[PDB]
Image 1 (cartoon, rainbow, N blue to C red):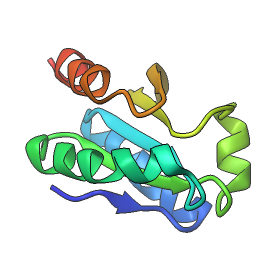
Image 2 (cartoon, rainbow, N blue to C red):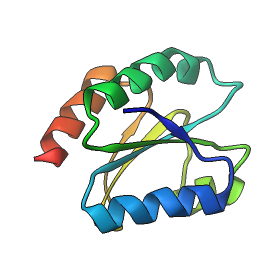
Image 3 (cartoon, rainbow, N blue to C red):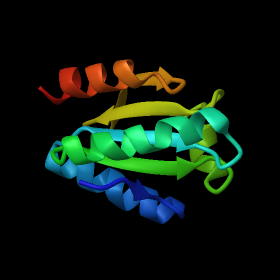
Length: 109
């Protein structure tokens, strides 16, 4: 149960495809190194990955994958997107710890 940093669009796509194929919830943390709030939520997101080995936890640095961030209309940092069966199903804008846990548990079933 580990957070996977996706450093290329190709890396992002292969893990996204794995989640779609296996029916697992995928949670993307859209983050930046300049971002204070992102730094704060980072260890919490890492801990969720350990607690939920049944879901896939991806990290996307918005300045590294500018095209992926744009595709997801990322307009505040951090933004967490929840993907299920290929589609966005939910989001959390900001380091809202409890909200993130709640949605993981609810969406995983």
